[PDB]
Image (cartoon, coloured by chain):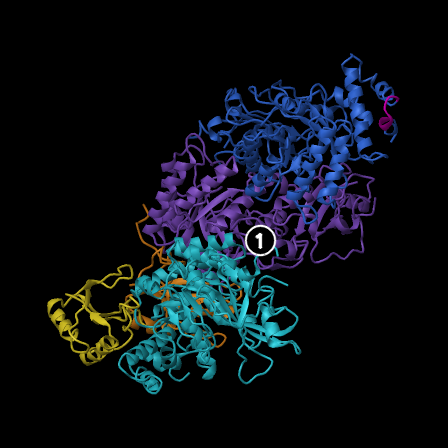
Chain colours: A blue, B yellow, C purple, D cyan, E orange
């Protein structure tokens, strides 16, 4: 072999670059495995259609590991298919035997190949225009408990969260339909809890109705029903259901005006390990090229400077048009998204009232903030627990719209909003 | 012992080859029920091919007599290489009362 | 917590068991992490009944020979999950629980879909039995080339390499991973110039030859118009990369192929992201059981010849899970739960390593009759082309099928029947050296 | 009450008569129970006109030889019931009236659908005449195996037992009651490997062979996609278990088979719940008239050979009701109302007892030309297999067809023509002893 | 050197023409696994034509004995112009365990 490691190949602006993180077996030299991670992701002509490696760049601070930049040509891949990028690139390359652990860190879809895709149905700008929610990061409950709640008692907990100024309310991962709660009746009693919570407080309330289904016929008849309840948004667990079902539902949600909340269910099978898998900034690029107006980007509050540099790394990749190659922040390739619409970055960890000054500064306006993730609820319920998370939101947006430095004057603006809010002042401590 | 691959034809094919006395005694069932019998000839006996060509008429001269039986032997001398039938006809129920081959090529 | 760790809980015959391989962060005890992997895959941390819908860890069983690792058997109830949705098994079980931060690595080893929950699925479109009845190919492991080169070939030159392999005794011929459609080779033309090359090689040599036409596509509409075209070319078989395209698109095509009589070749592309590390991910015997419940008449189970005794007992573990009706709990052979498939149809186990002529004793002995043997993946073809290259891969089959059917122990008398079949075949004798 | 017992009421030629067999509780007089079975099947116990929509008992006629039992002839008007709905005859007539508590047993013996109400229905898709014209099989009762064993056979082994029976002169071949689809044998594959076995046996021996493909299904969508597939295999005939699947699914498939040229074999599964007791239920001559009005070109009328004179006059009663245009009122032969069918097409009467070779004199004499003779139900096959077993069942047919067409009284000269046909047929001679 | 255009037939066709000792030793795999061997004959070996006609019965020797090729030699003398098979049958798995041609025209 060793015709797949071409280190003088300055890669074309139409190639589809991929930056693996190879950890080769002991005794395997770095030129030979980098020509091998470019080997079995192609051609297992050759000058026109081979994935070729063009740089090594060993990982600083660690031996026996490097970052093999592979340069796949454009015309190898299907126009508009992200299930052909992952079939071609990460199909038969992670199981190659001369590699102890292979991790796809980043990938560069060019301007030439982003234009074949749809992008999100609605961006940041188009989504906020449809919702008429401007200049603040949006909100969310997650209805706890997950299981057990019948379709109306689930809807009553949706009505109770959405009364308290909460923008959206998430349906769970494992709630698709189940003998205690069918989707036809979950969707009915939720859309009857939104038209009451939108009539009570005039804001456009929504619920991420889970349309993840066994088949693509049962997914679109689960989304064509959320269309005919006049629902603003649906959601879709996008890695258990795959990139053929998202791109089916992306093309639907753009062509039916429904927003799409992509949930990163089963994401951590394939990126939790720091040496093997597919890092989420590939999977965040992969669903910006399939659809999604939202994506969970986890949380920032329980992470160090490097682990939230990486977390803010792919948050810029799924939300900003042009992102410069900044390897310390995790982004390995300068990604030009070619005016593709953005995706929201949904913060959903164990965040609570006091993380509002950070998460309005870290995550900007273009964000959604979920709640109930790890925290022990609110002692007064849901409608006080959502008004706590909405006053503490807009107390931090009020201070941000007055120049107050929310890294230092942030805990002050919660405590001076606990005076003019009683539901906040009881979530002020627990 | 087994069953041979033998092509069989119609509603009396699973028999010995029908002699002339039997067919005289066969049509004497057809015309005695008030039915008009006929002769139908064809090149091949195909399952697709569901019409066979009528020989001169559904011939009839009296309530009961030799009508068909002489006409079949005239058709054996005319067409010695066609599948010859003898068919009955009902007009009340309006279907055939028999359809069986008297002669094969 | 420790309300989700019920160690006395004998699990019911209708629970959906799951055997994780938890590698907890230090200081996290084993019960409290195993209650946690039963926590965030259900009922997360009095509005309902907890004790009816909660996942319960019920046994720990520390892994022998390696501390900080155990096998948390979790017992999810039946009525937590959706009837017929294998993308709701994974959304429930491996959804929110691997990124759990008290755990350094978490590996879903095995999973027991009960008889109550297998019956909501479809199974394969066609089993081992109905696949062999449609193809009229009995008592031998079936075959396949893989068309090299992958990239670059136009659709007719691609179909000539298909027709050349399908002459010389090969049963199937695989379309590649990274070939769905691409500006050199569109699918409408690749499927057309392969149907014109099957019905030439099927009419020439009277066996029902097929080709795994790749219907993996960007959308589920584009997938089914890619499969309904392979239906209208009267193709026997399509294929689908079920882990890139997901389980919603696979179960859509499962239901399609059963309702259209097309065989489905499930290809395990992007499987090694999640089953290759021994500490974290989803072991393939979960993903083997997951597509026996959704569609597939064939699934790549890789190979055996490059692996140890322990690494092929585990590979012959999940070959039995996707091919046999009842499989006993044997953990040395890798299976953690006894699995009644409730007369669900089998899936072929496809052998697709870097394999050649001299592995026909091995892969007919290891993988039985109910198998498919791919070729051309790693080994460098044949000097006389594809049609003598495929007859070399077919005379070596039926020599090893004839030898196995005469008492000849192919483990020991296997290299004799390759050498005594290279005499009566000139196409095999030149393949006998490399 | 006794406003519903009008004993002077000469019923109109457009009423829908019904002859119950009322067994009233003691102390209930005969007129007041017969007015009651005319009550709760209408106009239950002024806002309307009662005298226009009420059911009127008009005659009592006590059953000879058995007290506490009579034959309440009820006269329902025409415009009470739906045009074309035989599931509204039963909802009106036998709907709310058998569970009536002043009655120990109530049996709907016979029912007279008038010429005015027969014309709203479709009849069979194809009659006796049009069924014989489609199959080109004239002047003999047609045939059928029944594929034993029922359960366990895969779809190709099932079609081999079909092809073996359909070689040796058999016309049809029945798919079983308890075979619709099951994890050993799906319908898409059972229909496929039977169409490949009809067109092999139809092309071999030039008769239009058929097979009663079972399109009985869970839903009416799954039934019609099961029948539209037997249409697209160009199958001549399907079948349908019309009392388990009901009269709404039958009349759906009636209208389908007429609009698609498929013959419909109606099977009387679950009939014996309601026609087997002599005191209570719905006599089969109601259910025979009920599917002549909805679909079916064939219906099982059971057998004659195991029954007395009185129990076969009643069986030849409803064979005439479903096969003849006009049938006179003869109560010893079981028929209670004279029934003009208004040129509605006939239904074949299928003989499917425990019958074999030696019953061909009996079932060509009793059941005439316009019949189908099943086999293999109770009798233990044949020693030489199915194709000599079917030629035994076909030479014995055409011996008894030839004998009947020569004046030979098969009642008395019937066992002679079996024995003198076993000489010229070796397949029949070994079936001549058992 | 090339590969000739040679029509091949079934699951043991890519071999030398199977002699009698081999087929006796072949069926001794079939019936020793508890399976049911048989003989199936046909005029042509077509990919479309997917049924072949079962010769007499799905045979069986006592638990293991030679009744199959001994009957094939009676079928080679009965039908010397048909594609003769020897097929196995399983009852548990319910498919054929072999399907191979012993005799060609």
Given residues B33 and C183, the one toward you in this image is B33
Residue C109, given in percent of the width and then of the height, sits at 67, 48
The tally of labels here is 1
Q: Residues within 10 Å of mark 1 (few under 14, many from 20)?
A: many
Q: Is residue D335 above or below residue A406?
A: below
Residue position for label 1: C322
- Residue C294 visible (yes or no): yes
Given residues A47 and B38, the one toward you in this image is B38
Query: What segment is highlighted magenta in the picture?
Result: A419-424
Q: Is residue C228 above or below residue D10?
A: above
Q: Secondary structure at mark 1?
A: loop
Parent chain of label 1: C
Q: Residue at x 60, y 19 (%)?
A: A321
Q: Is residue D106 above or below residue C185?
A: below
Q: Quadrant of the N terminus of chain C?
A: top right
Residue closest to the far top: A403
Residue D384, given in percent of the width and then of the height, sits at 39, 76
Quadrant of res A85: top right
């Amino acid at each position: 072999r060793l015709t797949y490691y071409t280190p003088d190949y300055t890669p074309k602006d139409t190639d589809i670059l991929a930056a693996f993180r190879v950890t080769p077996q002991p005794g395997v030299p770095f030129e030979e495995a980098a020509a091998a991670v470019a080997a079995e992701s192609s051609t297992g002509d050759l000058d026109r259609y081979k994935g070729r490696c063009y740089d090594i760049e060993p990982v600083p601070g660690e031996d026996n590991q490097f970052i093999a930049y592979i340069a796949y040509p454009l015309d190898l891949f299907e126009e508009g298919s992200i299930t052909n990028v992952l079939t071609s690139i990460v199909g038969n390359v992670f199981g190659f035997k001369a590699l102890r652990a292979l991790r796809l860190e980043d990938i560069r879809f060019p301007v030439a190949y982003i234009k074949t895709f749809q992008g999100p149905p609605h961006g940041i700008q188009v989504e906020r225009d449809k919702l008429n929610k401007y200049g603040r990061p949006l909100l969310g409950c997650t209805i706890k408990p997950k299981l057990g709640l019948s379709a109306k008692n689930y809807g009553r907990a949706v009505y109770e969260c959405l009364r308290g100024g909460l923008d959206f309310t998430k349906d769970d991962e494992n709630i698709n339909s189940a003998p205690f709660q069918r989707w036809r009746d979950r969707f009915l009693f939720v859309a009857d809890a939104i038209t009451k919570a939108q009539a009570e407080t005039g804001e456009i309330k929504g619920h991420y109705l889970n349309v993840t289904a066994p088949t693509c016929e049962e997914m679109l008849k689960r989304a064509e029903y959320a269309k005919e309840l006049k629902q603003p948004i649906i959601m879709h667990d996008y890695l258990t259901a795959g990139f053929t079902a998202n791109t089916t539902l992306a093309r639907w949600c753009r062509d039916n005006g429904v927003l799409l909340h992509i949930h990163r269910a089963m994401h951590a099978v394939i990126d939790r390990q720091k040496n093997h898998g597919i890092h989420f900034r590939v999977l965040a690029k992969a669903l910006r090229l399939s659809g999604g107006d939202h994506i969970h980007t986890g949380t920032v509050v329980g992470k160090l400077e490097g682990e939230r540099g990486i977390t803010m790394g792919f948050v810029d990749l799924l939300r900003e048009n042009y992102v410069e190659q900044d390897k310390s922040r995790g982004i390995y390739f300068t990604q030009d998204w070619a005016s593709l619409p953005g995706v929201m970055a949904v913060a959903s960890g164990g965040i609570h009232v006091w993380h509002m000054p950070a998460l309005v500064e870290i995550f900007g306006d273009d964000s959604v903030l979920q709640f109930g993730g790890g925290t022990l609820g609110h002692p007064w319920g849901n409608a006080p627990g959502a008004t706590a998370n909405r006053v503490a939101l807009e107390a931090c947006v009020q201070a941000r719209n007055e120049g107050r430095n929310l890294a230092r004057e942030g805990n002050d603006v919660i405590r001076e909003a606990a005076k003019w809010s009683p539901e906040l002042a009881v979530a002020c401590e627990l | 012992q087994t069953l041979p691959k033998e092509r069989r034809y119609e509603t009396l094919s699973y028999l010995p080859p029908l002699t002339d006395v039997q067919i005289e005694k066969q049509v004497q069932y057809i015309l005695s029920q008030g039915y008009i019998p006929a002769v139908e000839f064809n090149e091949v006996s195909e399952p697709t091919e569901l019409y066979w060509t009528l020989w001169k008429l559904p011939l009839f001269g009296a309530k009961t007599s030799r009508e068909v039986l002489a006409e079949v032997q005239s058709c054996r001398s005319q067409y010695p290489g066609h599948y010859i039938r003898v068919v009955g006809f009902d007009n009340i129920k309006q279907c055939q009362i028999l359809s069986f081959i008297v002669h094969k090529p």
